[PDB]
Amino acid sequence: DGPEKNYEKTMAILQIEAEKAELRLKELEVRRLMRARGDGPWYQYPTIDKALIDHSPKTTPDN
Amino acid sequence: GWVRPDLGELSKVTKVKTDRPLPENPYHSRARPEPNPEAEGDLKPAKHGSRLFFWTM
Image 1 (cartoon, one colour):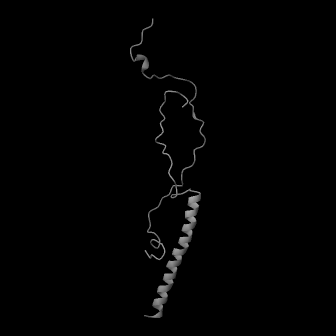
Image 2 (cartoon, helix red, strand yellow):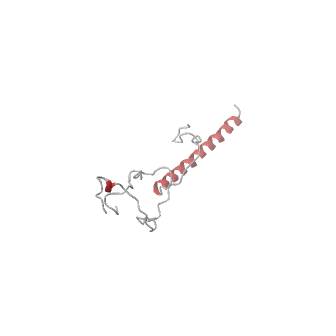
Image 3 (cartoon, each protein chain N blue to C red):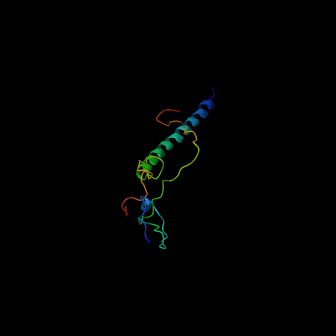
């Protein structure tokens, strides 16, 4: 096949690779930031649900 | 002019008007922490597949 075949295929190879590599670097950075700050979807560790608590009046007041 | 209350008569929960204002913050709670940043958006296909090492997809 003509040189244009291989060459046109290969810059597409390089573009896909680079658009994956900078994505990998940004993924490392995002994962670190979101493990440290935590203000986002993942790396959010569980907590206590607010539905378990009860607000109805109790036997003794001020509790 | 008094009557002995019947059994359970002086046990049902009643109501009473008090002119004092409502205790808006009985526990004197502070400002509640803001929630996590809400996220939305349809799932577009993951860019370049798994992107794990040499896997194309």
